[PDB]
Length: 164
Ligand SMILES: CCN1Cc2cc3c(cc2NCCC1=O)OCO3
Ligand SMILES: O=C(O)CN1C(=O)[C@@H]2[C@@H]3CC[C@@H](C3)[C@@H]2C1=O
Image 1 (cartoon, rainbow, N blue to C red):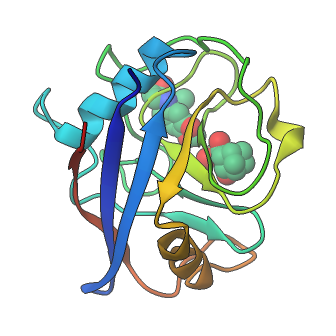
Image 2: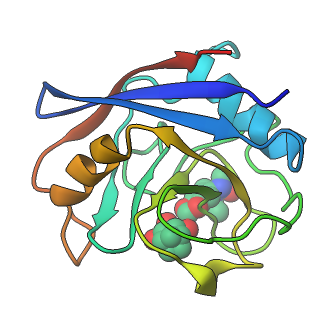
């Protein structure tokens, strides 16, 4: 019942590989549907050709600001922002897919993939999926990050979509 979506990612134009994500529509259907639709681009906008703007090694890889490309932008398929659906899923370890926000009830399109357990975020960021394959691709993305979050190469989602 849960969608599988994919991100194909490159660094300075050179392909890194494919990340496949399960979206937990069974637990957070509104939040899963937002991410799913932004991967397909079927509302006329989405993640295709946007960047991972903030990458911090031993923490997470953040992306999804397709409007401003600096982490101050992005929007949902519902409107500019939508409520925190629930906090049932937890930041249990590497590969967890969660929503970036600017406080309670400010979910747009920005998201992050954890490269460690980020349990401090539990109850503050809505977890809505995890990495099914391509965690080696996430580590490659991670390697181009820095402690400050600034990336050493331009990391781009060159293509994305839905597998099932
Ligand atoms: C809160 C301002 N703003 C943009 C935005 C920026 C973010 C974020 C979520 C959003 N929400 C979508 C629309 C919106 O209202 O997570 C971290 O940076
Ligand atoms: O984008 C922002 O302005 C704040 N922001 C981040 O820098 C990342 C890490 C800290 C919380 C989660 C993970 C995500 C987020 O919302």
